[PDB]
Length: 197
Image 1: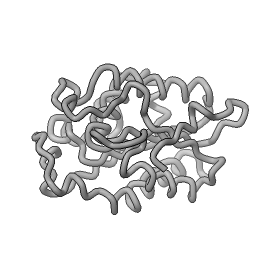
Image 2: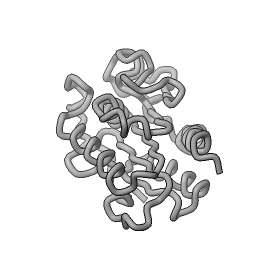
Image 3: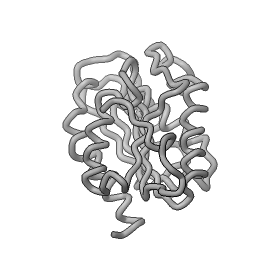
Image 4: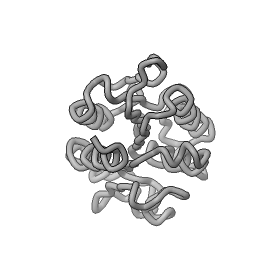
């Protein structure tokens, strides 16, 4: 449900084939918040419960609203926590395909972490989904250093954070349908593109 630590808890002798690392929005609970559980259930349907590990970004990422105003759209402590999880995935399961996502502050966190990542680990992330991306205008709909064909941004009309503001309006809270269908669809397609099946 809202906390999943499958990568931290998982046995290195029985690594999943796919590892999903997700950062929640501001003030959301657990480490998956409101959208992460919907994406997770559809990934487990596609790959099986033993086939995918779901890992939210917890620890030092407190998802504090005020940190949206900091230079990268989140805190340096939160970026170190998400980088640490990508590096743990790479060490624990070197053959797994990675996928990532984030909502709102979590989308800025996912973009900042991927930008800073060692390229050999960044290149293992087959697809990333971003909802209510707070750096959408500033980054021109891209994650720095990461290919456009592996990125999918869900930015609703009237969601002001997608257009350079930090005002929260009703369209910012309306990504439930996307998390239920097109966002897991995109991640599954990008994993199968490189792993076959």
